[PDB]
Amino acid sequence: SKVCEISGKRPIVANSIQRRGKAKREGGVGKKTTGISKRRQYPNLQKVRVRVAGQEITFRVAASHIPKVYELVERAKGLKLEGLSPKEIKKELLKLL
Amino acid sequence: HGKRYRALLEKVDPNKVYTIDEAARLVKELATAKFDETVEVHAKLGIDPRRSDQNVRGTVSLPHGLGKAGRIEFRNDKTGAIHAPVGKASFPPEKLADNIRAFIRALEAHKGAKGTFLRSVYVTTTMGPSVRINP
Amino acid sequence: ASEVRIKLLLECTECKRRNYATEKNKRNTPNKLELRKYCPWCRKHTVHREVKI
RNA sequence: GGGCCUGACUGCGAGGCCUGCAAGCCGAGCAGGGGCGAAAGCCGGGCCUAGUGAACCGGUGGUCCCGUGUGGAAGGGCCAU
RNA sequence: UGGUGUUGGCUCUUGGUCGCGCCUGCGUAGGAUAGGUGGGAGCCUGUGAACCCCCGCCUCCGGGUGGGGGGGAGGCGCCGG
RNA sequence: GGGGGGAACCUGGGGAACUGAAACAUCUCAGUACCCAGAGGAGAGGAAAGAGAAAUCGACUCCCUGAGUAGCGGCGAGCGA
Ligand SMILES: [Mg+2]
Ligand SMILES: [Mg+2]
Ligand SMILES: [Mg+2]
Ligand SMILES: [Mg+2]
Ligand SMILES: [Mg+2]
Ligand SMILES: [Mg+2]
Ligand SMILES: [Mg+2]
Ligand SMILES: [Mg+2]
Ligand SMILES: [Mg+2]
Ligand SMILES: [Mg+2]
Ligand SMILES: [Mg+2]
Ligand SMILES: [Mg+2]
Ligand SMILES: [Mg+2]
Ligand SMILES: [Mg+2]
Ligand SMILES: [Mg+2]
Ligand SMILES: [Mg+2]
Ligand SMILES: [Mg+2]
Ligand SMILES: [Mg+2]
Ligand SMILES: [Mg+2]
Ligand SMILES: [Mg+2]
Ligand SMILES: [Mg+2]
Ligand SMILES: [Mg+2]
Ligand SMILES: [Mg+2]
Ligand SMILES: [Mg+2]
Ligand SMILES: [Mg+2]
Ligand SMILES: [Mg+2]
Ligand SMILES: [Mg+2]
Ligand SMILES: [Mg+2]
Ligand SMILES: [Mg+2]
Ligand SMILES: [Mg+2]
Ligand SMILES: [Mg+2]
Ligand SMILES: [Mg+2]
Ligand SMILES: [Mg+2]
Ligand SMILES: [Mg+2]
Ligand SMILES: [Mg+2]
Ligand SMILES: [Mg+2]
Ligand SMILES: [Mg+2]
Ligand SMILES: [Mg+2]
Ligand SMILES: [Mg+2]
Ligand SMILES: [Mg+2]
Ligand SMILES: [Mg+2]
Ligand SMILES: [Mg+2]
Ligand SMILES: [Mg+2]
Ligand SMILES: [Mg+2]
Ligand SMILES: [Mg+2]
Ligand SMILES: [Mg+2]
Ligand SMILES: [Mg+2]
Ligand SMILES: [Mg+2]
Ligand SMILES: [Zn+2]
């Protein structure tokens, strides 16, 4: 799981904080932290294949921005895309952002 | 399920909530018989039926009264309700919406119990359908 | 104290405040403790009753 | 042993004992409201010396002191446990 | 390993609960299959009675209820054991 | 147009341990050392969806002060606007 091609979401570094005890709101003495360590939080990357100008274009995008792709496809209706290789097609789509 | 019971079935929208100054104009066309008819007002409560303090004990009536200042009784059941007389079939309008207006606010004057004391208050005649209204 | 010799408060029966803390044996004294005592709020002696601590 | 009773008080406390600290101990007397006694008086638990646990965190009952622009509320302070 | 995203179509059996209707409620005196309280001397019929034909049924085996085909003037309660 | 280099300085991405807590795990050391990417003679930041109580101020940076204050904190060691 890497980076979103639409939103640019990357993995972030987050802490897993291990806690113990009863919150003071629940009448307890309070929370004691029994461990902090680093983990990562990855974007919900998924594969999105779309047909644009006869070519099969696929995006690695976070699920959050899945529609943003289809939006991009609609925006590609007025583009001289015919003849192009999949790679440069995607570039044109991406450039519409 | 009589000839007059379903001839009031298109004098009633049982899927419509009314006000008090509009449910006395629609209980005279629902009360038409060969003798006089007690147009009965009923209501669902909101207390515990096995708690001995949450009972409804008392009397009213006024401004006007019965019909035959006519202190009408009203008491609850062993599953929570009321069932009380009267304001019979004319007994003029806007003096029937005025005798139906100082009784709904009587029983609400005998409340710390649990659950809203204002549920379902249906006004039906001796031989008619039931109007939902607003207590 | 012990399980059978408990701790308790005496609540002023008039203003319902707790002014005294003491102990009793609940096998010996199953009934609620009842004693007259000076309530600093009421500024007079008042029957005080055992309430749980 | 028996009557009445709740001082197994509330607000203070001169003065000391002990003592590195922190504690621990004894305490007359003044006021409040009481108990017993005709009264002098005595009564701030128990013949005495063991029967115990500093702070920190937090619970419950008061108080109504603070309340993050203002009124509240959350939260906390104080008294008690 | 549960929930959720990626993750959609159809079908069947389903369920929570919200409302509504039609119904189900038989310890014992008893007309006799009495849910809780209540209003109420009239109600139900040319919106077709009383007995029949197929009964959706339930039923403590006596009974409770509904539709239409036969079907043309009673039934059901007051009273009061 | 890019590529690579530059003592130290700078921003961004990542990011320790000894140590201190006279043991240790939350805390500390410290977002330090270090790795990486980028920038330039500087870099960052920068024209209020701001402060925060002044019915007030008016981009940002930098120094003095506010201040070891407010607070944070196994309310410990310490950290600290
Ligand atoms: Mg975690
Ligand atoms: Mg903590
Ligand atoms: Mg996909
Ligand atoms: Mg979404
Ligand atoms: Mg005490
Ligand atoms: Mg004792
Ligand atoms: Mg006081
Ligand atoms: Mg003796
Ligand atoms: Mg004695
Ligand atoms: Mg004695
Ligand atoms: Mg006396
Ligand atoms: Mg006292
Ligand atoms: Mg001294
Ligand atoms: Mg000393
Ligand atoms: Mg001691
Ligand atoms: Mg005195
Ligand atoms: Mg005296
Ligand atoms: Mg005397
Ligand atoms: Mg005296
Ligand atoms: Mg004294
Ligand atoms: Mg001691
Ligand atoms: Mg500590
Ligand atoms: Mg505390
Ligand atoms: Mg205040
Ligand atoms: Mg004070
Ligand atoms: Mg405020
Ligand atoms: Mg105030
Ligand atoms: Mg505020
Ligand atoms: Mg206000
Ligand atoms: Mg408080
Ligand atoms: Mg408070
Ligand atoms: Mg999982
Ligand atoms: Mg799923
Ligand atoms: Mg260069
Ligand atoms: Mg960095
Ligand atoms: Mg860095
Ligand atoms: Mg590492
Ligand atoms: Mg360490
Ligand atoms: Mg150490
Ligand atoms: Mg050391
Ligand atoms: Mg060691
Ligand atoms: Mg740090
Ligand atoms: Mg370089
Ligand atoms: Mg360059
Ligand atoms: Mg900039
Ligand atoms: Mg601007
Ligand atoms: Mg300017
Ligand atoms: Mg720090
Ligand atoms: Zn008191």
Image (tube, coloured by chain):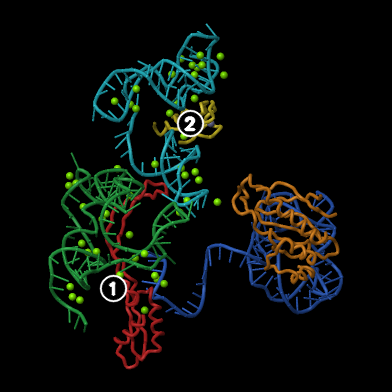
Chain colours: A red, B orange, C yellow, D cyan, E blue, F green
Q: Position of residue A41 (x, y in %)?
A: 31, 66
User: Do the dots labelled 2 and 1 sit on one chain?
Assistant: no
Q: Position of residue D15 (x, y in %)?
A: 34, 17
Residue contact at pointers 2 and 1, CB within 8 angstroms = no
Looking at the rendering, in which quadrant would you find the C terminus of chain C? top left
Q: Position of residue E40 (x, y in %)?
A: 80, 57
Q: Is residue C31 visible?
A: no
Q: Which residue is mark 1?
A: A2
In front here: B43 or B90? B90
**What residue lies at 37% left-to-right and 46% top-to-bottom?**
A29
Disc 2 secondary structure class? strand
Q: Which residue is mark 2?
A: C19
Q: How many residues crowd around disc 2 within 10 Å: few (fewer than 14), some, or many (20 or more)?
A: some
What amino acid does circle 1 point to? Answer: Lys
Please report, as a chain letter, where disc 1 is located. Answer: A
Q: How many marks?
A: 2
What amino acid does circle 2 point to? Answer: Asn
Q: Quarter-wise, where is residue F75 in the image?
A: top left
